[PDB]
Amino acid sequence: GSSGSSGMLITVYCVRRDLTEVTFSLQVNPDFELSNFRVLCELESGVPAEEAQIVYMEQLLTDDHCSLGSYGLKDGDMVVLLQKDNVGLRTPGRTPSGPSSG
Image (cartoon, rainbow, N blue to C red; front, side, top):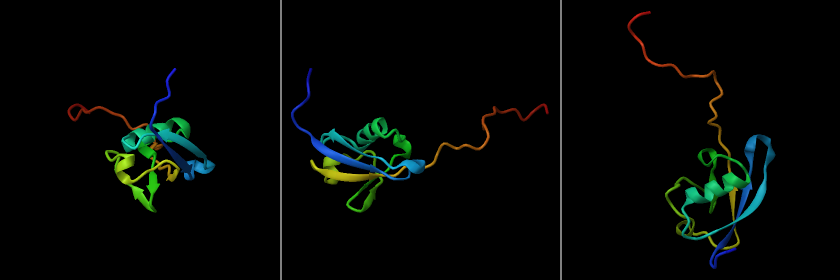
């Protein structure tokens, strides 16, 4: 089919992952939103973009709106993936309203 033309290698390094730690590479563009890079790492590693972190330059990237090229990502760069906890596994919380009548 087709491949593309321009792109940059982005190495990801998972840590926590609930005891797993995985290391894989990805091929994206410099004009690719961070969120996009997450969905990818979320497709490879599996970590949820929501609970998917991206560390670069020693500083944690806290912007999904920002892009890769913007931050300063080039072909042959490496990043660390940190998995958070937001599965909220504490009883099935879900109930409608109803003050009157009890």
